[PDB]
Image (cartoon, rainbow, N blue to C red):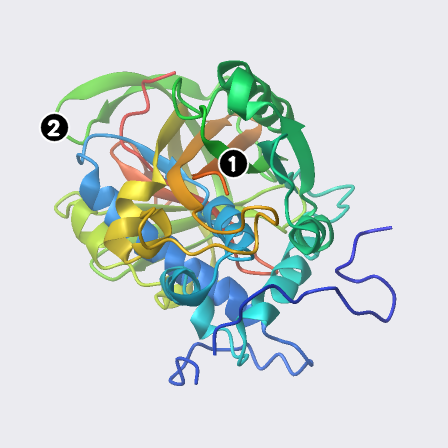
């Protein structure tokens, strides 16, 4: 069994309460993937536009000397899970902000199928490759009878089991139970996401998503060619880092405005790490400000195995934030206003007032001699009740693609590596 996605020949129970809907029309392409639904391609593309669109926004909100790291795929999954229960305008905005309107189908109900199609085609049993894994769960207050078909399109399409907690009474204790589920599901890395008073008396459903990844480098680094070196911080100050070094053949190009893009694949070429180390004289800010997921030229043009002598800090960056600030700026407004939020698919017995009170995300990355472990979580809580050389020793951005499907699984700016 490997879920609904590729059952046998098949069909799924997907039909929520409301449906939205003319697509983007120009571009929003497909890799000449003549196959029935090769929508999953345009889903990954839509998803990756939101990833760039969400980073450009978060990076602007974040002081340039801070590290950023998120898993745009975690963020698109946890909200497409919530768009099941949405309706009317809340739905027009979830389709619009997360770019789901770009997938060429005429109806929002379809996107859910295509997400289970790309998820099955992503966390698959790769007994060589790596460890890319996800776990979605819907925890709701024991006292609310939840909507039965919600409950189930979630079992099928997202693998999200309902778990009753006693939010209403024992909410502080309930926060500890979800926070620990996330710990377990990310191999103890994304610890305590949900901040101290985020869940209380009136939380109806907390829904959580996770994504964990471990991968060994193809071309490992030697613990002996690991000297300390200065990393010249984003602010022009510097710190001592344990800087890894190796000589190898790797995909590479020096792209627009001498912004070097390296791809270092993990064990058995499915997942890679992309590093964008922009020239000395530039500022990573510029390259952050003009990022466009249709700058995939950058990525796909370095199919030129090139002999690098690579220097790279081994670091550990950990980060968390509120997706509610930046999504509001992105345009998702109705979903968070108790006034304007329309979500009738989630509750049966009340069915009405529910809104997203806050929405969190925490992330992790340890890159090191033998490989890297990344982890990520999102919980959206809802309430209402009813010898060329590439010496990366200065800030750079990090992508972690899953090549086959092209899905930016994680994205970051390691701007200060001498943190733990």
Image location (x, y in percent) of residue 351: 53, 51
Image location (x, y in percent) of residue 152: 72, 52
Label 1 SS: strand
Q: In the displayed structure, would residue 145 be above or below residue 330?
A: above
Q: Is residue 222 at least partly visible in the picture?
A: no
Front-most of residues 164 and 108: 164
Q: Is residue 81 left or right of residue 225?
A: right
Disc 1 versus disc 2: nearer the observer: 1
Q: Earlier in the sequence, mark 1 or mark 2?
A: 1
Residue 305 marker: none
Name the residue tied to disc 2: 236
Image location (x, y in percent) of residue 211: 57, 38
Neighbourhood count class around disc 2 (C-alpha, 10 Å): few under 14, some 14–19, many 20 upward: few
Q: Which residue is rendered at x = 45% and y = 30% of the image?
A: 202
Front-most of residues 89 and 125: 89
Label 2 SS: loop
Q: In the displayed structure, would residue 106 be above or below residue 384?
A: below
Q: Is residue 253 left or right of residue 110?
A: left
Spatial CA distance of label 1 from label 2 is 47 Å
The reply to whether dot 1 and dot 2 touch (C-beta < 8 Å) is no
Q: Is residue 165 left or right of residue 327?
A: right
Q: Which residue is rendered at x = 63% and y = 40% of the image?
A: 134
Image location (x, y in percent) of residue 223: 52, 18
Please state, as top left, top right, bottom left or bottom right, where the C terminus lies in the image. top left
Q: Is residue 71 at least partly visible in the picture?
A: yes
Front-most of residues 90 and 96: 90
Name the residue tied to disc 1: 204
């Amino acid at each position: 069994v490997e879920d609904v996605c590729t059952a046998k020949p098949r069909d799924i129970p997907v039909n929520p309460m409301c449906i939205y809907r003319a697509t983007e029309g120009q571009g929003s392409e497909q890799k000449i993937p003549g196959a029935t639904n090769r929508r999953v391609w345009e889903l990954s593309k839509a998803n990756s536009h939101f990833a760039t669109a969400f980073y450009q926004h978060l990076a602007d909100s974040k002081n340039n000397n801070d590290n950023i790291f998120l898993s745009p795929l975690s963020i698109s999954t946890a909200f497409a899970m919530t768009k099941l229960g949405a309706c009317n305008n809340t739905l027009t905005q979830l389709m619009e902000v997360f770019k789901f309107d770009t997938i060429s189908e005429k109806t929002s109900d379809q996107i859910h199928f295509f997400f289970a199609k790309l998820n099955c085609r992503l966390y698959r049993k790769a007994n060589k490759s790596s460890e890319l894994v996800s776990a979605n769960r819907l925890f709701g207050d024991k006292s609310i009878t939840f909507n039965e078909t919600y409950q189930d399109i979630s079992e099928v399409v997202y693998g999200a089991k309902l778990q009753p907690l006693d939010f209403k009474g024992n909410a502080e204790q309930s926060r500890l139970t979800i926070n620990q589920w996330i710990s377990n599901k990310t191999e103890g890395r994304i610890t305590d996401v949900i901040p101290p008073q985020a869940i209380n008396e009136f939380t109806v459903l907390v829904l959580v998503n996770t994504i964990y990844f471990k991968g060994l480098w193809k071309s490992k680094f030697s613990p002996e060619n690991t000297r300390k070196e200065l990393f010249y911080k984003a602010d022009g100050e510097s710190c001592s880092v344990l800087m890894m070094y190796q000589e190898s053949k790797f995909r590479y190009r020096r792209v627009a405005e001498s912004t070097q893009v390296l791809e270092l694949p993990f064990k058995g070429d499915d997942i890679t790490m992309v590093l964008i180390l922009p020239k000395l004289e530039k500022t990573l800010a510029k390259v952050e400000q003009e990022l466009t997921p249709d700058m995939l030229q950058e990525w796909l043009d370095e199919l030129t195995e090139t002999l690098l002598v690579v220097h790279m800090p081994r670091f550990r960056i950990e980060d968390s934030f509120s997706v509610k600030e930046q999504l509001q700026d992105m345009g998702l407004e109705d979903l968070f206003s108790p006034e304007k939020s329309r979500l009738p698919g989630i509750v049966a017995e009340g069915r009405s007032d529910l809104y997203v009170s806050d929405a969190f995300h925490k992330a992790f990355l340890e890159v090191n001699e033998e490989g890297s472990e990344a982890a990520a979580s999102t919980v959206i809580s809802i309430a209402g009740r009813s010898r060329v050389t590439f010496k990366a020793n200065r800030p750079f951005l990090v992508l972690i693609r899953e090549v086959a499907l092209n899905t930016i699984i994680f994205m970051g700016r390691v701007a200060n590596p001498c943190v733990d």
